[PDB]
Image (cartoon, grey):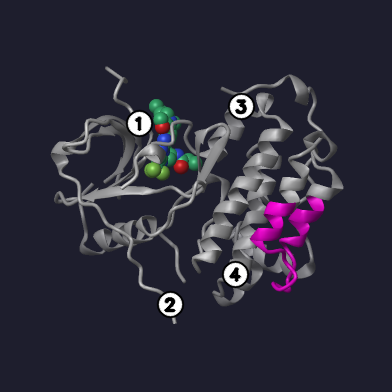
């Protein structure tokens, strides 16, 4: 009983963009930094291009991600700019210059303040709440799949596995392949734990075959050193077995937004107050100001 998806899918000519560098590499496909110029529009857009050789099942994976990226518009979700129909189909999205958030809290852990951490949790809940409003389920929410546009502004990404990573899975998901927005709240909880530990690996050492039994006993990830019981309690609530008991993303916005209004009451970071995080570029425009 759903509404017609009238999102526009833009096909871009290979001539419209230049690849400047390789950002990330796999045999399946590689990600490039690059610039894109709409043909008649006199702008330059910093983009990231995802692309190697193609099994017939390979192209069906990238197109589902493009279908999902093209139907979302939210300040905290990565937006598709278009696709290019060269022999290996290219997905073209907005360049998130500071890279992936997991890598970012590791590289800068000694300059990351409680106000940023609480803002990222707010921005991520907003993204996920937008996804729940649009009746979507991520299935792979993790700090590795949140990208950093500025240090003030993160966006959720990786919709390849989206529908309508065992250490980020919900227990119901691990036992019975069940996936909900509430199962997404679980991985939200694990995602916040990664940030509060500056990128620590959850259940480090423990093999994934062991994860299902542990969680049944009642064990959970431990309270991060910087976390007041308020923040840690919210994580723990995301990890209830009864999924109706986990919080909704709209409540996580409210709660973490309440805490982002006085961040040092809720995260205790040594020296928290002192820390601060940052051709021709004349016709340059960020994707977020390029509207169609
Ligand atoms: C959590 C790991 C991860 O997702 N890493 C990653 C690596 C490559 C591409 C993407 N996807 C992506 N990336 C950007 N922006 C981006 C990522 C990484 C860098 N780095 C780190 C590594 N590096 C070298 C030389 O070793 C170069 C700098 C830089 C940038 O942007 C300048 N933007 C968008 C995506 C997207 F998700 F694919 F759209 C993720």
Among numbered discs 4 and 1, the one appearing first in the sequence: 4
Which residue does the numbered mark 2 point to in the structure image?
Answer: 2
Q: Residue at x 71, y 59 (%)?
A: 251
Q: Secondary structure at mark 4?
A: helix
Which residue does the numbered mark 4 point to in the structure image?
Answer: 174
User: Going by the image, does 1 lie left or right of 204?
Assistant: left
Residue 12 falls within the magenta-colored stretch: no
The residue lying toward the viewer, choosing from 261 and 68, is 261
Among numbered discs 2 and 4, the one appearing first in the sequence: 2
Q: CA distance from mark 2 to mark 4?
A: 29 Å
The residue lying toward the viewer, choosing from 251 and 212, is 251
Q: Secondary structure at mark 1?
A: loop
Indicate the position of residue 61 as horizontal and vertical percent values: 32, 61
- The numbered dot on residue 108 is 3
Contact check, label 2 and label 4, Cβ < 8 Å: no
Among numbered discs 3 and 2, the one appearing first in the sequence: 2
Indicate the position of residue 165 as horizontal and vertical percent values: 54, 58
Label 4 vs label 1, nearer the camera: 1
Residue 242 falls within the magenta-colored stretch: yes
Q: CA distance from mark 3 to mark 2?
A: 44 Å
Q: On screen, 176 above or below 261?
A: below
Indicate the position of residue 124 as horizontal and vertical percent values: 59, 49
Which residue does the numbered mark 1 point to in the structure image?
Answer: 285
Quarter holding residue 280: top left
Label 3 vs label 2, nearer the camera: 2
Label 3 vs label 1, nearer the camera: 1
């Amino acid at each position: 009983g759903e509404a017609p998806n009238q999102a526009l899918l833009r096909i871009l000519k290979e001539t419209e963009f230049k690849k400047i560098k390789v950002l990330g590499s796999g045999a399946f496909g590689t990600v490039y930094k690059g610039l894109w110029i709409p043909e008649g529009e006199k702008v330059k857009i910093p983009v990231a291009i995802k692309e190697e050789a193609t099994s017939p099942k390979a192209n069906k994976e990238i197109l589902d991600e493009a279908y999902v990226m093209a139907s979302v518009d939210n300040p905290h979700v990565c937006r598709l700019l278009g696709i290019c129909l060269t022999s290996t189909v290219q997905l073209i999205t907005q360049l998130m210059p500071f890279g992936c958030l997991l890598d970012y809290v590791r590289e800068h852990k000694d300059n990351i303040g409680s106000q940023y951490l609480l803002n990222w949790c707010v921005q991520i809940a907003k993204g996920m709440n937008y996804l729940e409003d649009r009746r979507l389920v991520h299935r792979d929410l993790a700090a590795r799949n949140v990208l950093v546009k500025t240090p003030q502004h993160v966006k959720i990404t990786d919709f390849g596995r989206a529908k309508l990573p065992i250490k980020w899975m919900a227990l119901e998901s691990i036992l019975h392949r069940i996936y909900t927005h509430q199962s997404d709240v679980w991985s939200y909880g694990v995602t916040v734990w990664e940030l509060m530990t500056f990128g620590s690996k959850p259940y480090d050492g423990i093999p994934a075959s062991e994860i299902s039994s542990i969680l049944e006993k009642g064990e959970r990830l431990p309270q991060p050193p910087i976390c007041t019981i308020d923040v840690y309690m919210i994580m723990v609530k995301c990890w209830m077995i009864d999924a109706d008991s986990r919080p909704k993303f709209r409540e996580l916005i409210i709660e973490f937004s309440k805490m982002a209004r006085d961040p040092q009451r809720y995260l205790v970071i040594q020296g928290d107050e002192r820390m601060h995080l940052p051709e021709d570029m004349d016709d340059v425009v960020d994707a977020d100001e390029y509207l169609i």
